[PDB]
Structure formats: C-alpha cells, structure tokens
C-alpha cells in the first residue's frame, strides 16, 4: 500500500499536545526540532504545509510556575495567552535553521462561519503559502473557549483543511490509528468507522475534511520520521480517502453558497482568460455590475450573451465593484481610498460553468 | 508644587497605546521598544497595571519578507502582519524579560467584542492576566478583520481595550488628531481618562506617572463606577435572576467581594452566560446586578456548592465565581 | 395630578389578556379600537401591543386549558395571532384606520441592522397614519411566552415613545405617582416601566375596567399609577448614541448640512457629505464632523461607508442609478441623530 | 407520466405574486384555498408560502406605483400582510380549515435554536390539522424585498418541515430547453444553463437537499393542484437524488457534535430501534459533556455503542436536572418546560 501523502502537495499537519509537551515540564524542544526538520524536508520537496500545533497551555503553565493543569477556564485562557508566544518562538527558531519563515495565526470556528472573515483568513493563508511561509495555526482562546477543555485541535485541523483546500490532513497522535486489527485504509465518512471507535473526534475530523476533497491520515507521532516516510509513499497508521475530488467539491461548495441577488457581466477577453488561461477575474474585465453582493459571497460571472461562464467568491462589494470596474489594479487605491486584493475573484475561489 | 498634575499619577490601571511611527524605523526600532519596555516596567514596579496596545507588525513583516515598500494589496498586508506579529512580540518579551516581567500576546477584533460571551471571555482572560502580574500585549487580528490595517493605527482598539478592562486611563503616545479625540470619547464611556502625548518626549510615561502633565489630558465626565452602573442598567434582563442569602448580601455590600455559587439560595427564570442579572435578597429586594458566568440551568446544579465541587457536578468548570466583583454593581 | 398622557404625542398601548379575553371579547376590543381611534383623531401616534393571541388560538383549537408545553403554546400563538388581528383590523376599519401586523423578537432588536429596519418600518407606518399592532414572534423565540409587558417596553424604546400605557385588571401598584425605576417597587409591569424609562418613556399602569380610560388619560385625568422617567427623551437618545458609537469611521459634512442639522431640525442627506473616512456599516452609530474637524452630530447610518462614498454629493433621486438599488433617501434620519 | 405529487403526503405550495395579485385577486385566492382544502381532506399536509403582501399594502395605502424607497416597501408589506392573511383565513374557514400566520427570515433558520423552534411550531401545527401560511419578515430583513418572490423561502420551508414535495406555481409553463422539460433530476447542473426561472431551479436544488421533490407548473392551469394530486403530471417535475430518510441521516452527520452526548437505557434503546418512538428524559441514564438546544447529539447505549443521533430539545445542564423524570415533573424542576421529549422521533435517526 502506497501512502496518499506521496501524491499530496498541500498538507495540514496536526500535532497533538502529548507529542510536543513533556508532561508538567513545558515544551519538548527536541521533539519540536524533529517536526520542524521533517516539515522543512517536505517544504524542500515542494509541499505546502500548514501546521496546527498544541502546547500553548503547557508552555504557559511553565512560564507562570504552575505544576498542574488548571481546572478553571480563565486560568486556562491565561496560560494559553502566555504560552502561545513561547510555542511559536521555538518553531520559528528550529524552522529558521532550515531557512524557513513561519507565521502565527489565531482563528475561531466563529470567524470561519462569517463570509467576510472566512475569505480574509483564506486569503491570508493562501498568500502565505504562495510566499513559501509555513503558517502555524491555533484557536483564539481569549475569545472562544469551547475547545479548550477537552479538544486537542482535531476539529480545527479539518476546518483548516477545508479553508485552504488541502490535499491531505495528517493527524499525528499517541494512538497507532483506527482499530477494528489496525485499519490501514478506508473511505472517509463511512458510518462503520464511527462504530469502530479521542479516536472518534479524529474520525469525525476526517469526514469533515473529506467535504472539501481532503484525504486524512491518522498516525502515531511516536513513529520515527513519520512525515518523511508518508511523503516517500510508505503507509503508516490509517488512511481515509475522500469520495469526492478537490475540484468537484469546490463546484459543490460554490453551488451551495451561490446567491443570485447580484452578479457581474464580463467581456470576451475576461471569459477567455478564465476558461483557457486558468486566470483570475480582474476588475478591468468587468463590463457591468447588476444587483447587490458583499465581499465573501459567491456570485455568477455572466458573458455578454447572458450565459453563466463561472462562479466564485467576490473580494469586493457590488458598490465597490461599480467604482473600480474597467480600471487597472494600480488605480483601485486612488478610486476607493484603499485597496483589497488586485483580483475581483481569485482563480482559487472560482469554478467554471 | 502648583504645576498641573497628571491624572496618570492617580490611575492604577492603564492602557498604553504606542503609534507605528514610534516603534518602527520608517523594520522595528529595537532600542525604542526597549525604552518603552523599561518605562512600563518602572510603572509596573510602582504598582500600576498596564496593558500595551502596540503597532509595528507590518513593518516587521516587511523586513522579514525582504520588502522595501509597504504593499498596496490587502492580502500582502495581511501576510506581512502574520509574519511580523511573531517578531514584534519576541522583541517585547525579551526587553520585558530583562526587567523580570512576563508578557502575553492577545489578538482581538471589534467583532469579537460585539458578542456577549466573547466579550466576557476576553475580559476574563485580561483580568486574570493582570491579577497574575502579566503585561498583556494586544493587537488586532488582521488575518480575519482588515479595518485596522487599511485605515487605522489602533486608536479605536486602545479605546475598546480601555472599555474592556475598565481602565483608569488610556495613554495615546504619538508623533505630535480626530480619530484620537474620538477614541478619547469612546474611552470616557467607561469612565477612562485619556492622555494624548508625544512619544518623542523623554521618559514620557515615568514623568506622567510622577504627576507631570504632558500633552493633552481629557477627563471623562462620568466616573468608573457610575459608568459601570449605567452599563449594567443598559444590559439588564429580567427573564431570570438569583436569590442570595444574607451572608452573600453582606459580602457584596460590605466586603467588596464576588458572588459565589455557595451564596445562591435559588435560581428563578432563565439566563445565559454573559447576560446581566439581578441578585435578589430573601425579601425580594434587588441588592446587586452583574454579568453571570453561568447559565440558569448550570447555576441550578451548582447552587450551594463550594467552587471545588463544580467540576464534579457539571463535568467541567468555568470560573469559580457566579458573578465576579469586577462585573457587578450594588442596587 | 395631571396625567402625563395629555402631553404625550406617541403612545405604546398594551392591553392585558384578562381585558381582551373571556377566547376573545370582541365588544371589549371594539371599545379599545374606538378609544385608540379617538386618540389617532386628536393627533396621537399609537402603537398597540396586544395580548390575547394564545387565548384566541386555544379557542380556535378547542383547548379549554392553557397548554404547558411550549410547542403547543407556539401553535396556539400562531393560530390566535390571525384572529386577534382580524378583529382589530375590522374594528379599526369602521373608523377609517389602517392597521399593520408586526412580529418582533428581543433578538432582532439586538442586531444593529434589524433594529434599524424595524425602527424605520414603524416610524414610516406612524408617518402614514397606520396603527401598528405588534406581537412577539413566538415561532422563533420562546423566552417570553414561557403577557407582553417586556415587549411593550422594548417597543417604547424602539420608537422613542413618550409613554407606555399598560392596561390591566388591577388598579395599579395605591401609588398615584413615583419615579420609574425606583428599587422599592405586578412585578413584570414595574420592571417594564424601568426598561421603558431607559429611553425617556413614562409609564402608566391603569385598570382597563375604568370607563374610557385612554380618553380620560389623554384629557389629563390621572388614573392608576404614573411612573415618570428620570431622563428626558432627547437626553436618553444622547446616552443611546454614546452607548453605541463606533469611531472606526465617520463623515465630514459641509456648512449647509451643519446648519440644516443644528437649526433646521432636518436629516443628513448624502448631498451634504463632503467626505467618508474609515469604515462603517448600516445601523452603526457614526460621528458627523465639520470642516474644522469638530464633531457636530452623531447618528445611525442607513448606508455603509463604501455606499456612502458612491452617493456622496448626489441628490436622493440619483442614488438608485449609482448603486443599482436604494435604501432610504437620508444618510442619517433626523429621528436617529443627536447634536454634538 | 405520473405526478410524484400523488405519492407525496406533506406539501409546500408556493404561489407567485402574479397569480395572487391583479391589490389582491380574491377569487383566485378562493380557488387556491378550495384546491388546498380538497388536498387537506384527502389527507395531505399542506404549508402555504404566498406572495402578495406589498401589492395589498399598496392598495390599502392608496399607492398606484410600487415604491422605490425601502421603508415604504416595508410599510406596504406590514400593511398588506394583514389583508393577505385575512383573505386566506376567510376562504379556508369556508371549508372548515384553520390557518396560522408564520413569519420567518433565512437568518432565523441558520441559527440552531431558532431553526428548531420554528420546526417544532410547524410540525405541531400540521399534527393539529392547521394550514400554516408562511411569509418573510420584511420588517427586520429586507434582502429579498427588491427581487425575491419567495422561491428560496419555499425551499427552506420544505427543508424545515421535511416536505415530500415543493410545488412552485408560476406564470410560465415550467423549464424550457432554451421544448418544455417534463422530468429531470433536481440539482443537475444543466438545468441552470437551460434557464425568474433560475431562482426556481436553485430552489429545487435546495429543496432536494432534504429529499424533497419539486414541481414547477403554471398556476393558470385549471385545478392544477387537484390534477397533480390525482397523478397527472403538469409542468416540470424535478426528482431529488436522495430519499428523505437518507437526507436526514446525512443532515444529522453534517451537524453532529461530540462535545456531549447522552447514555440511554435498554428500554429507551428498544423504543427507539423497534417502536419508532421519541427519546424521553426518563430513558436517559447519564449526560456527558456539554450541548445546547438544537445541537445534534449521539445517544449511546450502556455498552458505549452509538445507537441513534438527533436534535436535542434541552441543554446538557437542563437534561442533567430532568434525567429519569417523567415529563409532567419537568416544569417543577426547571421552572418552565419546553417539549416533553428530549429528542423527538422526527428529529432523530438510527445508527
């Protein structure tokens, strides 16, 4: 059996607390260095990697002089805010040794339910990946505490995979994988995987991830060089395959969120760029703006004949689009007093027909 | 002797906001950050509670990404912010560490604070950090909200943080004004005074704290406690409340203390975490009012129990208090 | 004691279940309709918050006992709301008065956009001489069904009523007069009076069994208990604007607009906007700044900052062409702003 | 070709503005009311989504032209809503049928608690043999006022009540190749290309998410609803790819959280698995973790196996207070009660 990771370019890697912390003595800096070295080697093979890592609370505890994990939520939130700085600094240092830049990101599930904040976060992350930066993502425990108690960032991992359209979510944990005999391969989202089973949340995370076409691997982080070995095509732990491909999931997602209160009409030059050139839709290609829409909504792109040729997430409101239509991107700032992205609809946020 | 006294000398809890220009060289000015850190450290050691709202993340990001010109596109600005955030904080942590001070990084947006639960969660985080003697360092979360990067310099954030922690004073350190005056108005709504002063003034924070007035001082019309009473009245709901015993009433009225689950005799009606509820005596008289940490159903389960028993009863715990002292008013 | 109702132009009238029900007492509703019609003809603006929906629903569903389960209460409310309104519409129609049905929840009113949308609907209905009839939307929120006293007070806040009148079975609290919100004081009716006073609205609690009670109060005769708000309507409006003010964005307005606002008691129109700074959304409270940079007013914006950028300096009849749609003609309605 | 409506028990009937307005066409409303009454007497459960409020409002306010300003549109809607319902109530009353007015917004239905509250209201009304009449609440949300004709609302109501079919009655015959399409799969991409037809096709796709089929037919057709219910196909019929129960299982899996659950006894397990019944508080042995009204939770047996999952009526704290208690004791314990069930049979699936 070949690991699906060998054919996956964009990976979300989720590392459990137990793997990154030395129970009661803060962070295991050596283990983080090993993860950093592995991720660096993936990055040098051409993979795009986002890291979802726990350990903030344990580091916070150490820095505050607490020997025991606090039971009260406020002390947990405090420890998280104190520890987040340390956890990232360690990752930055170890990644710097390999010439890799990192970034800290804090998200909540709420943010991702809002159309504007979803797009803002997606755009941040895709831009960071384009620039070759490794984003490091955590929950914002100062404002949302739902996952602080019992969660270990499994749901966050799947949400991040959806958010960036990852090819695969890798959950590195203490357990070997799913047991019936260890299940080496199965279909993500299959009912019986739930019966067979914090394994359950990881299986549910795999189902959520498969909604966007992402596959999932659940493997022990105690396995030596586990990420390299998966990337080399060696199957380790349990591999769950999404039923739907990334582009088909994207088309369903666009249809699911499509609104028809407004749209844009685009010229032939823009139509050709979209259909043949694999390009973004720019303001200059917009001939008219009809109706109303807001940043982050899904709108139809209609040709002169009135046929829908594409649909995608708009970066700009209909009123903003009205102001900047037919203008080159370098003129947007003068017209609005600010600019957002140069594209009206980014290529990564649209589908044909 | 008679020269105008700075309100900062009598202000225990301060929000200090430092402009981009002060903290950046047109990357980061590490020496200038050290000076702010040294001044804040001296305030901490005089007994002040300080929260820092600092800009500079984009400039640091630019330097780390090899960009000489500030990007015009929002996504490149957001990327620079996420890169720069890591550096900005590490510098502050280092310079504060030289004075024995712990820091924490906090990211907030105005959207977060518009939700009752998230507002209480953020408030509770910050007040717990101040209790532990940590200096919180607060920035906007530019990954999800791009208003601050686009048009701002964290003036509106400073005033929101002052409201959030009930600061005695917001200090806006600048290069030299409308957004800052509007910030002072917003800060005064919770009873916070504002000082607008040039950060190019030598030892400006120490001199203010020593009682020397510098720049412009704006005094809130309403005091902190009176602003709190108006805020509670504004948000009060009467769908539910708690009845509390005489021991709890005395602790609240005389002792300046929190309302604990053990003092709750009964729970009437319905309420949710982050709502404002009345605390009623056996005679049916409202004696206090405040933000509840727990729902009415949760409160029913834990009433009359010591805080160490909450976890066993619920399967989890939130705060040990039902209503923290900082989140309640009398009558 | 003179009744404060005599100098109150905009009234929220709340009629209790016992008064309106035996199902429904159609004759008693006719009497309330006739009284409200007479107030409307003296020039009062009246919004009605009426109970009775559940009782009517019960009758129409053949239920003799008030149901304990919320689902059955929700059903009875939805069934009964149709009957309760149809009766009111008929009786008001006899006097030439149009009515409208409005369903609101406390949640709606916590959202900045829905608050403004509801307020704007109601103020427009009042301008057109319609009597709005308001009920809770029990289909979606059940916190209150589980007699509309809280709703009355929220409506008074929403439309800036001069007075809330709660008509009940009891004579009052007898206290003839007191300060609304005074700790020492039915309980839900007193708490409603306190909530109402937060927008400057006074409250009267009086027995609906008193003959011609609304007319007599409007003539200046005090009946039942009168609770006076500590703060006036304009001062409460200023507190409400300060409470909701954001400073992420604002508008700069010209001298002509400043004068219309300060002297003329008028709205801020797009044509008076010289510039749009920062960011804001419909339903947020923004500062209006003059050429010298001084804040001269603050109010609820009908339009986002991007929309305002598009329509600044344009007459209202041109907004639709520029945006592809229009909202209100005003950027900030006169009823939704304060000076300084 | 047989109409799917003949085998559909629970119907959402959506009637376009043009059909119901000239003000209001009272005679045309009487005809719809008579047809719906006949369906109701054959045992169908019918929810009506009708337009017309703004037109009625305009008439009552003396306006000959549709207003451009949103506030005047909102006012006309509020005025017109009263008339539109009173007409329907009168005509239905002539056939012995009770009606109810319901106002919903799409936002309401995105919130877990408001969704359940609305679902519960409607299912209770249908059980009681009432015909609900549903409209958008234009007082609070104006997104749909400009261009919408309640097509999206119809589909959301079908999802909400798990309708067997959505019937959209319109001025046009149905969907055209650019030939009338008699039959197709709901949600098929090419139906969108073939096309306010587009919003109706999108409505059919949305409706099919809960297993509801859609019929789009001309309301100018004589006795159109009776003829469909008799099995005569008229207009365009769009068939959902997924069945109602399978869509319900997917919906439950989509919304499942595992932050909390309940453990239930063998008696409750049997009632669920064999008896097709609800989960009552009395069958709950323990409450683990945290959950809120409207969330989807697992029901676990003593052996730790998930046997069902469904929408909870109560929070975990409230469930803790009322576990093992008969329904008549809930009110004393909580100070209020919601539904007697912890998870209604309509809101759960077997696992």
Image (cartoon, coloured by chain):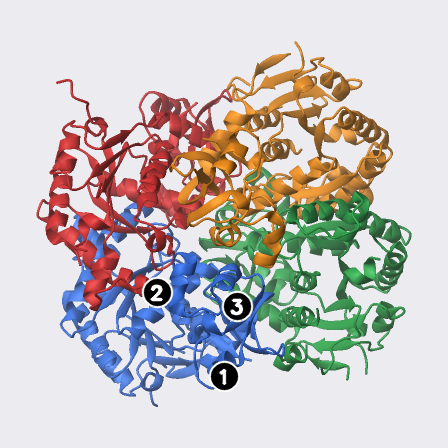
Chain colours: A blue, B red, C orange, D green
Q: Which mark is residue A298?
A: 3
- The x and y percentages for residue D239 are 70, 77
Does residue D207 sit above or below C223 in this rendering? below
Q: Is residue A196 visible?
A: no
Q: CA distance from mark 2 to mark 3?
A: 21 Å
Disc 2 vs disc 3: Cβ atoms closer than 8 Å?
Answer: no
Q: Residues within 10 Å of mark 3 (few under 14, many from 20)?
A: many
Q: Residue furthest front?
A: C256
Q: Residues within 10 Å of mark 2 (few under 14, many from 20)?
A: some
Does residue B148 sit above or below A349 in this rendering? above
Q: Nearer the viewer, residue B305 or D137?
A: D137
Q: Secondary structure at mark 2?
A: loop
- The x and y percentages for residue C1 are 65, 9
Q: Which mark is residue A272?
A: 1
Q: Nearer the viewer, mark 2 or mark 3?
A: 2
Q: Nearer the viewer, mark 1 or mark 3?
A: 1
Does residue C93 sit above or below D284 in this rendering? above
On the same chain, marks 2 and 3? The answer is no
């Amino acid at each position: 059996m070949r690991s699906i990771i060998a054919d996956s370019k964009r990976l979300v890697v989720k590392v459990g607390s137990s793997l990154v912390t030395n129970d009661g003595r803060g962070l295991d800096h050596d283990a983080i260095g090993r993860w950093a070295a592995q991720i660096a080697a993936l990055r040098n093979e051409g993979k795009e990697v986002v890291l979802v890592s726990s350990g903030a609370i344990a580091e916070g505890m150490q820095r505050l002089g607490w020997s025991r994990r606090p039971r009260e939520i406020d002390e947990l939130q405090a420890a998280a805010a104190v520890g987040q700085m340390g956890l990232a600094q360690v990752y930055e240092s170890r990644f710097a040794e390999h010439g890799i830049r990192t970034a800290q990101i804090l998200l909540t599930h709420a943010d991702l339910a809002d159309r504007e904040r979803y797009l803002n976060a997606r755009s941040t992350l895709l831009t960071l990946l384009r620039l070759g930066v490794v984003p490091i993502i955590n929950e914002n425990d100062t404002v949302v505490t739902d996952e602080i108690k019992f969660g270990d960032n499994d749901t966050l991992g799947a949400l991040v995979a959806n958010l960036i359209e990852g090819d695969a979510l890798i959950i590195l944990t203490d357990q070997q994988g799913l047991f019936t005999t260890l299940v080496a391969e199965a279909s993500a989202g299959a009912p019986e995987l739930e019966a067979m089973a914090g394994m359950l949340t990881k299986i549910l995370a795999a189902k959520r991830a498969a909604h966007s076409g992402a596959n999932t691997v659940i493997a022990s982080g105690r396995e030596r060089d586990v990420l390299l070995r998966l990337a080399s095509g060696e199957a380790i732990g349990t591999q769950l395959i999404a039923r739907t491909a990334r582009m088909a999931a994207r088309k369903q997602w666009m249809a699911d969120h499509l609104q028809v209160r407004g749209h844009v009409v685009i010229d032939a030059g823009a139509v050709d760029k979209l259909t043949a050139g694999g390009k973004s839709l720019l303001p200059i290609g917009v001939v008219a703006v009809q109706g109303v829409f807001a940043r982050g909504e899904v709108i139809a792109c209609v040709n002169d004949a009135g046929r829908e040729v594409a649909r995608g997430i708009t970066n700009y409101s209909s009123a903003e689009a009205k102001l900047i239509q037919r203008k080159p991107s370098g003129e947007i700032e003068a017209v609005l007093g600010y600019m957002l992205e140069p594209e009206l609809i980014h290529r990564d946020n649209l589908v044909l027909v």
